[PDB]
Amino acid sequence: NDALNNIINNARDGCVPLNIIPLTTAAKLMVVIPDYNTYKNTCDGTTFTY
Amino acid sequence: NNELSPVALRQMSCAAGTTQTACTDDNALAYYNTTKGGRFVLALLSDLQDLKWARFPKSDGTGTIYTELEPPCRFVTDTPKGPKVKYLYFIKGLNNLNRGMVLGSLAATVRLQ
Amino acid sequence: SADAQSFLNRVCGVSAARLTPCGTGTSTDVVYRAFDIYNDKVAGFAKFLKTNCCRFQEKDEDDNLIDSYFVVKRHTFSNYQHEETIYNLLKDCPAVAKHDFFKFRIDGDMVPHISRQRLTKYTMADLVYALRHFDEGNCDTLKEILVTYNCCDDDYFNKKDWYDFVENPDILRVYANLGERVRQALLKTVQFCDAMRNAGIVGVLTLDNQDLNGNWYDFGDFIQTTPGSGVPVVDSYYSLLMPILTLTRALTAESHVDTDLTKPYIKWDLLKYDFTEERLKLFDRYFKYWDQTYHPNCVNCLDDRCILHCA
Ligand SMILES: Nc1nc2c(ncn2[C@@H]2O[C@H](COP(=O)(O)OP(=O)(O)OP(=O)(O)O)[C@@H](O)[C@H]2O)c(=O)[nH]1
Ligand SMILES: [Zn+2]
Image (cartoon, rainbow over the protein chains, first blue to last red):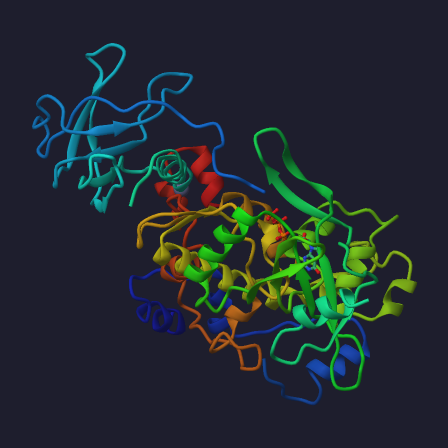
């Protein structure tokens, strides 16, 4: 209830799209990888950016 | 060719004003069209210089609509009379094809300037 | 003797005019093309057979043919004066092809010709007809159009099911290469409508009077009115062209910074959801003379027909 409040107050009338709430306030991320070629382009190493 | 209304149309008669009930007897060469479902006028011509309103009578007589007009345009005509000036109007909301129809017929059947 | 080699250098203008005849002498050329007709006894959108035209392709420095034609048409003397007057009124628009009126004798009499310069081989109805009446048994026009504009190469069609949408979904990427041409054609159409309104000319716009570069011609069915009171009729044009606007994705350039396909994308904030003004700006930019009220939000519509129209 702090990140959600922080992004709610920035809205000009209190309404925000639902598709950007997990994108900016979630704490955990889950990735499903088909094969190794896709793996080495998305989550290579120990830290990645998304 | 895609052309603009070969078979033409017929007629122009009746009235006009500027503030609702200002239409007294007849102040408009209200032009054209008697459609197949009933008389539906297209173009308005005015020997006067400023009108915002008209009242065309039809069928029942009790049903005669107080039409809202639009800002006018002006031109001079090549009539045998000589110097003759009107101020053109169309009934508001008239789509482009209808104005093209009446303008083409007026320009190609009768002479203007 | 003379004639062919004198008509050639008379059609040859004053700019560079490296011309070559399209298998003719002084006679006309016959082709099979698509038109949009309405003349009180016939109507429709079909493929008729053109009859009165002589075409000269243009060369360049290394003597290899290019996509430029000088398509002269032969018609009536009254039509000569009418078209000359309308063109003289409309010649300053940058969206109007360059006309050239001259007179030349084929016999003891003198007949008039009208020559148009630097057109393409196909028009925009040819493209619309090819895409809206698809038949894999014979689609030569579509293949020619695709290969002459660097959308693909001639060996792309050696594949089978190259046209299918479920198999080979790469045909979408192949088709999406004409969107910029379509967008430039739309902009030139808006320019032409503005010029017609300012000059006081009344006429109806069809797809077969515009080539694939956007230029306009054929003012044979227009009339004249007082300046500032012109009115173009653009119903059939937009209505028939509409299904092609999404197949080729013509509005892709509108997601870039300056409507330029070489700059990065626009970065909207994630909290914006209205976009009610961008829709109006797009409508005013690409559909200015479409005369029917447009509601960005379908909650203000009057009935189901208006809902369909605005959706
Ligand atoms: N762009 C282009 N069109 C061509 C060519 N050859 C034939 N055409 C066809 O020929 C037409 C050339 O224009 P016009 O014949 O002036 O058009 P139109 O609408 O038939 O003319 P009017 O009968 O005078 O109203 C186009 O509609 C094309 O369909 C060509 O080399 N280039
Ligand atoms: Zn609506």
